[PDB]
Structures are given as C-alpha cells and as structure tokens.
Amino acid sequence: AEYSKVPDVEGQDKQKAIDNVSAKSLEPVTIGSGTQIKAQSIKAGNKVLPHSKVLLLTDGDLTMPDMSGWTKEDVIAFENLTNIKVNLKGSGFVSHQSISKGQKLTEKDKIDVEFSS
Ligand SMILES: [Cl-]
Image (cartoon, rainbow, N blue to C red):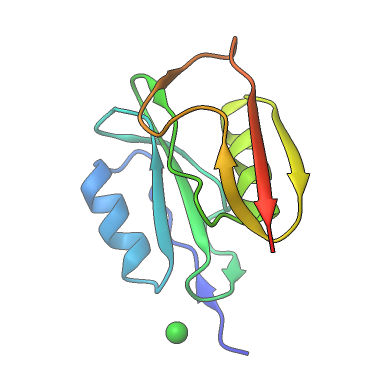
C-alpha cells in the first residue's frame, strides 16, 4: 500500500500549488477564482492514497467546482473547506450537482449532490 505525502501549499501561487500537489501523485482541485491558495483540505505532511484529491481554496470569490465522479469523502471535504452545506443522496460517485461548475458561491448557497454506483 503506497502512500503519497501531502505538500504544504497554503499561501502559494495557484499554479505552483497545483504543480506541487500533482508532483506528489495527488489530484489538485481548485475552488475559487483567485490566484493564491488560502486553504487546503488535507493537512500538509499527512499520508494519503495516491491519486486522491486535495481541494485547494483560492482567495477571491468562491466558485463551484465540477464534482462529477467525486466520492462522499471529497464532497464532505468541500463542505468543511467552504462552510457551504451539501446534501448527499445515494452512493458511489457524483452523477449530479445542483449548481453548475464555475458559478460564484456565497455562504448563502446550499448544494444537492446525487451519487450513482
Ligand atoms: Cl499510481
């Protein structure tokens, strides 16, 4: 069971952070329309499965990611990172989200996601 070590990318330039996460054989997913990373979903230094997702919250506006194919773990990480409540329905992988990718979000919004096996 090989593990990846999550890098510390908080405060980094967005593209540098994406590159640093990818270099650890992890999948960076950015949230927001900013140019600098404000927060990461996994504590730096932690061992996680290769190719698992690290959510990266930018500065500036929050925007909706493409959650297609996400696990419950991933969607729950999004709720904790953004303080936007997500309602989960079903099991497997995300097959529907109630807000389209790219839309600006506020803590006024709520998301419904459906999972399919
Ligand atoms: Cl691999």
